[PDB]
Amino acid sequence: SPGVFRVAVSSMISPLETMKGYGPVLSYIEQQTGRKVELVQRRTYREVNELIRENKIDLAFICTYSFVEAELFGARPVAVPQVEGNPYYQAVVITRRDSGINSLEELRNKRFAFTDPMSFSGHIALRGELVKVDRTPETFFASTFYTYSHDNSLRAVYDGIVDGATIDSLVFRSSNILYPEIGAALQVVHVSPLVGAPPVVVSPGLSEEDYQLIRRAFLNMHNEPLGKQALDTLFIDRFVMVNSGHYDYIREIAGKI
């Protein structure tokens, strides 16, 4: 009798390994709710946000900028991940060490990779920064491309297809371990201000009781056997309460457009 519980995620973070990564947390949500869980994947964060707006899903793992837009149509924050190292989050701008392009400023009239249009670390951080010099990516760079992948943006800089890219600090860190030939060739030439971890949200339609039940389940996940397995599989220490202030920098550059 309980209705299906739908969880939306981006298909482009871990191609071919998304159900592999999320499977245990979907099983945890089934244990805590008694509802069958369906994983809903989309290539773009615009598509995921429209599913949230239309109440076509219950819960979504969205990126930070997606969250700023989603809150304005009544998406409610559940919790934020705390990752091993209890890290901080920023956009890093990367070039090749051998490019002779040693600053964000020197990428004027150069080729640049973004990820998703609705990504902070993959797009909006750079668009926001360029307002300071009365420019947009289109009027600052020779050309831009949306790769829809932090890893593919990284690869495009490595292969000399673009001169620079903006990507997630955590993805750069993780990629430098996995791919050391690529790591060795790349340099961070600019870092953005710090912002909060990407929040988990529920759709505006979900009941107050369902919201409270799911929030409790996330905030208590690290104390449950199935929850610990879910956290280990996503390489997350635990989920903690959202601090709205952590996204105020994103809200401010969003307003300057």
Image (tube, rainbow, N blue to C red):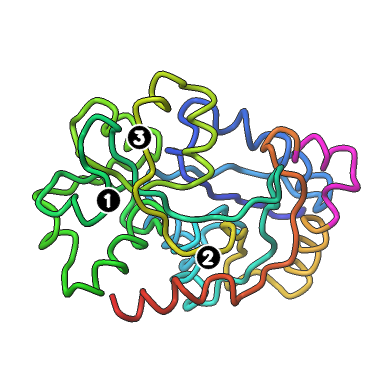
Question: In the rendered image of this protein, does residue 152 appear above or below residue 220?
Answer: above
Question: In the rendered image of this protein, does residue 144 appear above or below residue 14?
Answer: below
Question: In the rendered image of this protein, does residue 242 appear above or below residue 103?
Answer: below
At label 1, which amino acid type do we have? Answer: Ser
Closer to us: 113 or 11 = 113
Residue indicated by mark 3: 154
Lateral position of residue 215 relative to residue 173, left or right: right
Using the image, tell me which numbered label, if any, was put on residue 55.
2
- Is disc 1 surrounded by few (<14), some (14 to 19) or many (20+) residues within 10 Å? some
Determine whether label 1 and label 3 are within 8 Å by CB. no
- The location of residue 3, given as percent across then percent down, is 69, 55
Closer to us: 99 or 81 = 99
Per the image, is 146 magenta?
no
Q: Determine the CA span between mark 2 and mark 3.
A: 34 Å
Closer to us: 44 or 176 = 176
Query: Which residue range is magenta in the image?
Result: 220-231
Residue indicated by mark 1: 103
User: Please, what secondary structure does the residue beneath circle 3 have?
Assistant: helix
Determine whether label 2 and label 1 are within 8 Å by CB. no
Q: Residue at x 59, y 58 (%)?
A: 197
- For residue 91, which quarter of the picture? bottom left
User: Please, what secondary structure does the residue beneath circle 2 have?
Assistant: loop
